[PDB]
Amino acid sequence: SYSIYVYKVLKQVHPDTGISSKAMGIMNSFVNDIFERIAGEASRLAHYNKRSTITSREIQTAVRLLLPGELAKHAVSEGTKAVTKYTSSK
Amino acid sequence: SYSIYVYKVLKQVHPDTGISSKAMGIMNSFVNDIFERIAGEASRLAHYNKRSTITSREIQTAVRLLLPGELAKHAVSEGTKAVTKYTSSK
Amino acid sequence: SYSIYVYKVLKQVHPDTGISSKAMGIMNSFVNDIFERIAGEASRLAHYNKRSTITSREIQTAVRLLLPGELAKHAVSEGTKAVTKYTSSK
Amino acid sequence: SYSIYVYKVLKQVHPDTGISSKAMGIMNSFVNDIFERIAGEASRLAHYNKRSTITSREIQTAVRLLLPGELAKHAVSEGTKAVTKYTSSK
Amino acid sequence: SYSIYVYKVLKQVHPDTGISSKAMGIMNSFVNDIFERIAGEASRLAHYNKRSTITSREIQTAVRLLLPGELAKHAVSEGTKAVTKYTSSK
Amino acid sequence: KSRSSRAGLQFPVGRVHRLLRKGNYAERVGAGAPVYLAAVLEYLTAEILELAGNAARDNKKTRIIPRHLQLAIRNDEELNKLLGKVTIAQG
Amino acid sequence: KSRSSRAGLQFPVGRVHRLLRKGNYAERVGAGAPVYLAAVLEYLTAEILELAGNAARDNKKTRIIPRHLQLAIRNDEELNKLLGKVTIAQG
Amino acid sequence: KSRSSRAGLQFPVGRVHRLLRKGNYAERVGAGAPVYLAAVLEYLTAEILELAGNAARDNKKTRIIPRHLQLAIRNDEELNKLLGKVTIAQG
Amino acid sequence: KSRSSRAGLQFPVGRVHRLLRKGNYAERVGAGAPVYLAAVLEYLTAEILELAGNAARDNKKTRIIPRHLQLAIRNDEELNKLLGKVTIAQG
Amino acid sequence: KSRSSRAGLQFPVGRVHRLLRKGNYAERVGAGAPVYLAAVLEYLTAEILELAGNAARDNKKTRIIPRHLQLAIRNDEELNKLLGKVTIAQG
């Protein structure tokens, strides 16, 4: 389901280290998991603030809430970097 | 007591790795243990819901209650997969 | 003090592995310790139940109380096995 | 940002062991972090004691508060040693 | 400060294993530390019991209070053994 | 044909079925109950047996001894909770 | 051009966008939402995949098996919190 | 014949029997008491002695030194609880 | 002459001094403040850098990579508290 | 003859005696006080020094460096409590 991407990311990080199908299974579970987690909080944040739309501002706060200390700081940076490129990169 | 099966399962997982008699003793203790545990909760669940019969629906909830996080998710999948085959596989 | 026995038990378990005098010191401390512990609880159990004699039934309950989970189950088995042999083995 | 200094300190401690750029990134994060932490408490201490200036006496108390047990004792020594040299070393 | 003694004790325990100056620094910190700790409690015990003198009986109780489980038992033995030799060994 | 094979399992569905009623757990146990339980038992068995087999190789051996079960169980964070208050003899 | 490339990412922005609305999380999800989420997903993936790849080398192998993901996740103190109540199959 | 042999044990039933009464634990201690206690003592001894012997081999030696008892006790999760507040000299 | 050299330090006293006032921490920061802080920063840097360098050697390398900082920080009980809620990227 | 030798000790009984009174701990410290304290100090020194020496050998060296004291202290469960809030420089 994500195998394509996770493999693409793998080569990007270790361009010589392969990954097993069973290990790929795990990676896929991980991706779906934290997706479900983040979108859950994001959705929760939106209802609390009586907003009908999930902004990126919700994904961010959700990320701050769910992710550990410094692991969260990067995720925010990466997301802002990414969002900003996309928006400007019309 | 389970030695037959646990050995059968072993070859299925590691078709070249043997197991000691003493280690087999442990495996048997494990099987009886979690059996006792699961059937105990299942039975508990049935009395609470004033049902005279232990359905597979009780084994499942019992499994959710006793087993850890993600270790429980598979056990449910495996059980549903298994139950369904048996029911259809008349 | 127990060195004789603990050595006898050692050969029984590892008939080729020796033990240092200093390590033997420790083993002796261990034996006296848990002896003191078990007899203490046994004695406590007897006074609570206003019994003037320490039965093996007290040593057992004491063992259940002081020893961990499954480590206790064997100790009871071993003790019952042992007590029963002695009683029948007149 | 601190790379110069942290490298200078590195040679001083291990004059033959290099450090990666990525690892240098971490070191820089560390330096800024505990700087932010210490100055934060120092600043907090000054407002509490209604002082408009952050003395070295605040950096010290801040250090005692934020740093672990014995790791704090050295930091105080080092700072006092350092401050005193500078003051006398006009 | 204790370097003489700690070295003397070292040869007594490992008559072939040396110790670094920096490691010796640590050992000295250790000796002064637990000295400060033990004498502190000893002193505390004496004031509580309105005694103007710190007896060895205070050093002992202090040792029981500050030191762990079995690590304390030896320290008491060693101290009693030591005190007794000195007293008799006039 | 075998209830264990119909369910595609190794563990004895039948045996588990006997144990459920003998045990006096229930008044009457359903049909899928033992097959589900047998299924979970086989799963967990395979799980710990797998990790155990790995540890056996990692050292140097072919036979799995208690030490492996132990090292296995304790190292998996999830399995360690399940068998938290369990003592592996010679583990 | 691709939304995933416009954002300089590997993970499918589009897919993530579908999942956000299908999921019935929101009434309407914004434009940057999936791109931010896709971004975080890719990041975390790279992170654990990196540490995992390291552990694979450290032993002796080229293929990353669950054991590596496990050893990886459990050894990073920060990642261990995130996947605290997670069980790595064959980990 | 020996009470220790009649009970199929190594540990001194007799000695344990003396200690139970001398100790002023009880008013009168029964017959099976020391045999049960002696039995448990021997068991636990064998247990830790086994794990200890293993650790001795695992390193490289034939003689079990305190380090082994320590490494042994601390690694078994169950034994570690029992001797939780115990300090192994030179362990 | 240099304030960093007058204080016998490597870390930039001056820089630290700028950061203290820019930061809007204080109304006016004293003279010894940055020199003390710079001193503590250099100390801690040397500390973790030392332990890190050790771990680098212990494996087999000459360059210190994050893994070393990690292994270093986590193994020192005291440093582990300080950077308790800190995540070392690629650590 | 020496008070340290009369008590069969290495640690300076006399010194410990001076420290007890100088320290203003007591009004008057008894005769056995320093000898008992000196005794405990020497004991603990020998203890950690022993375990430390072991770790030094286990690696490959003859000189005990802080790392050994650390590894030593942290591995003994009992010593780890005593020096729980202690930071071993370069440990």
Image (cartoon, coloured by chain):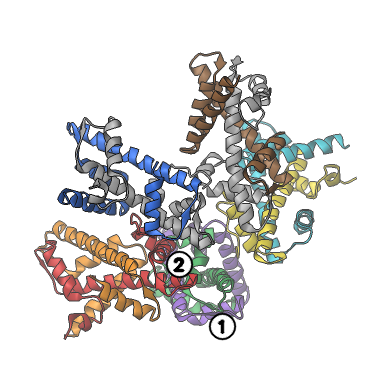
Chain colours: A orange, B blue, C brown, D purple, E cyan, G red, I green, J yellow
- Tell me where residue I40 appears, x and y as whole percent: 53, 68
Instruction: Give neighbour class at mark 1: few <14, some 14-19, many 20+ (Cα, 10 Å).
Output: few
Q: Residue at x 70, y 41 (%)?
A: C25
Q: Which mark is residue D34?
A: 2
Q: Secondary structure at mark 1?
A: loop
Q: Residue at x 62, y 43 (%)?
A: C13
Q: Which residue lies under the disc numbered 1?
A: I2
**Type of amino acid under label 2:** Ile
**A75 displayed left or right of C35:** left
Q: Which mark is residue D27?
A: none
- Tell me where residue C28 appears, x and y as whole percent: 68, 37
Q: In front here: D24 or E11?
A: E11
Residue G56 in view of the camera: yes
> Real-space Cα distance between discs 1 and 2?
24 Å
**I26 displayed left or right of C9:** left
**I86 displayed left or right of E81:** left
Q: Residue at x 22, y 53 (%)?
A: B81
Chain assignment, label 2: D
**Type of amino acid under label 1:** Ser
Numbered label tally: 2
- In this rendering, is residue J1 above or below D12? above
Q: In front here: I79 or B82?
A: B82
Whether discs 1 and 2 lie on one chain: the answer is no
Instruction: Give neighbour class at mark 2: few <14, some 14-19, many 20+ (Cα, 10 Å).
Output: many
- In this rendering, is residue J51 above or below I44? above
- Tell me where residue E62 appears, x and y as whole percent: 65, 39
Chain assignment, label 1: I
Instruction: Check the image and name the residue furthest to the right.
Output: J1
- In this rendering, is residue C42 above or below B2? above
Q: Secondary structure at mark 2?
A: helix
**J66 displayed left or right of C50:** right
Residue J79 in view of the camera: no
